[PDB]
Image 1 (tube, protein in one colour):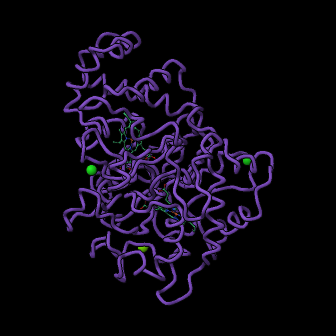
Image 2 (tube, helix red, strand yellow):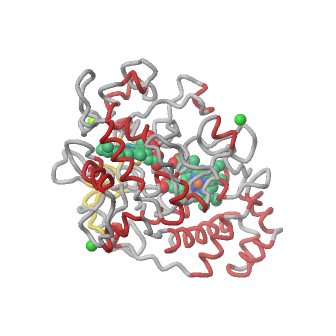
Image 3 (cartoon, protein in one colour):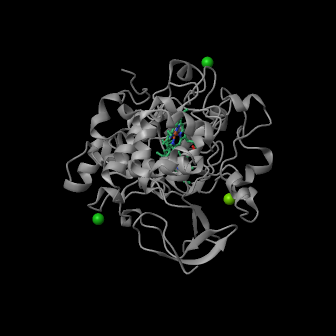
Length: 419
Ligand code: HEC
Ligand code: HEC
Ligand SMILES: [Cl-]
Ligand SMILES: [Cl-]
Ligand SMILES: [Mg+2]
């Protein structure tokens, strides 16, 4: 096709090729700020009701909010068992856990549909977009099927069973009131309209507040501290932090939405294995990220994408209880320190081993060793000092939306609060 629309309301994008089974390659970068969100207010309110309804799990008692706490920027507040164990959300039953850490859902409306784009300084197109860290859902409506029917999360047996359960409650009556009686008879329609309602909620302005001190710096040049400005400088310095090369920002713009702190692209940084995750009880099992989606979509040579994961946005990062797709780090400073010394000090991060412990041998070539600061060899000085790392942490704390600032720690290596 000549064009494709990758975010709601956005200008159509020129398609220059199709990769595998329907993934468009576009001619220009998607600008997430060009999207236009106009969710129907009562539809959004219905989606919010769904989001907080604990009847939607098996056994009952777990809602979306059980892993996406509104008091923590819709990132998980871990159960005591999860905090002591794998550091990813607990599912609907004791001893069952998500396969990955759950992100904040604030700003999720800006995640575009899957597409490829080849920058001027690139030999091949790169993948962007898709929901989940492996991009396996193209839209928010499609995403909903994941947690609802995952035995380790909300654990509904089938769409039919979920439909029967909902149909018997006030939620079923409300859905039938808006959509008509067939939502109580057709399980496919039930799932689809739940997705439409959830999409409206998650696309509402409530779910993209832009209320951080960084945002006040962008809109009004309200001053940050000298330390925070040192961290901002390191963050956009290609020779020190180089963070801006993947966690996109525009600190000279005046619109906060030009700073989402991700380009929604993918890379392979090889964070350490979290052996507390149930799936990793098999030492031959690895969560390989994007290549599972690439295989499903018949992208050519799909294992080139093994160990690739979607670059997360960093807004509200400093109130999370664990970090990276596998929750392996429990402090923000450790995540930043890892970026700086994975390549120079692998034994620190991989239990004395000199190379990655969560990437199969076959896929080690996929790991990024070219981007600063991951491009320095063992025994050479890292790009940044421990003081630089502290300053980066100080800067990342400016990305917390106003209502959540009290959850942040004060010590550079501190953990988010559990009030
Ligand atoms: C804990 C058991 C979960 C429950 C209950 C819900 N979600 Fe969640 N969510 C969870 C994890 C571990 C992740 C990441 C999984 C991965 O493979 O990356 C997610 C992700 C999402 C997303 C995508 C966010 C993104 O890619 O940026 C969305 C939009 C989302 N979750 C929505 C959502 C809904 C609406 C829920 C109730 C129906 C729901 N989640 C429950 C963990 C858990
Ligand atoms: C592109 C090559 C990257 C650069 C340069 C930096 N980061 Fe990044 N980051 C990248 C990816 C692919 C991921 C996900 C990895 C995973 O296993 O999940 C990350 C993750 C983060 C995190 C975790 C955020 C969370 O929500 O869990 C943090 C805190 C982070 N990165 C910080 C960070 C800093 C400060 C950087 C400059 C020193 C930086 N990253 C560079 C990809 C890329
Ligand atoms: Cl447990
Ligand atoms: Cl602007
Ligand atoms: Mg490579």
